[PDB]
Amino acid sequence: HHSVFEDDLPFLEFTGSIVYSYDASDCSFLSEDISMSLSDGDVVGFDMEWPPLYNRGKLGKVALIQLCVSESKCYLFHVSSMSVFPQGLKMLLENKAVKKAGVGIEGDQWKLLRDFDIKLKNFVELTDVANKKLKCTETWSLNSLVKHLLGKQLLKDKSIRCSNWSKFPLTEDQKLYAATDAYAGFIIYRNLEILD
Image (cartoon, rainbow, N blue to C red; front, side):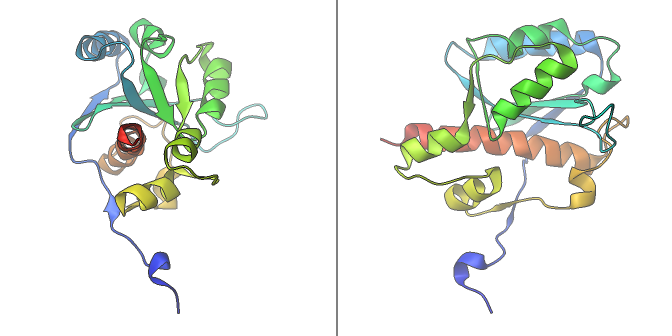
């Protein structure tokens, strides 16, 4: 038996526009589109993915970067398929003008620097934002925050979450999973930020 709190909730699934990009210049211009749609201080949901196999003692190299810039649009930048890391994306990630939200985001900063020599700037750990805004002292996970604030749970097929994100092209399931994780970050920040 189990309590209501332990019941299986519906799955969170992004139903907006998922922009899939796998070419460097396309990505750079897309990054400029994002910049034209935001103003200083705006926050986007952030997340990334990497393949399963280990490389020289570390996690597989980042293969996908996701940016949810609004409730109806999320970008999937399949950098593992790009000949060079898109300059426009680099500038966007290193731009203090745009805040990036997520969980375990500090770890993402480290891996991003190691894999591409890019310095993620102005990121916010959702765990801290929640504790501050919800006035508590909990150890949150993206999933527990989604349950608490949205009454839903994150898609959980392990074979998909740990799939070969470097394989081109991404499957519809991979795109949905990746997009929704960044979407969760965006919605959580927005819902928390409004409180006061």
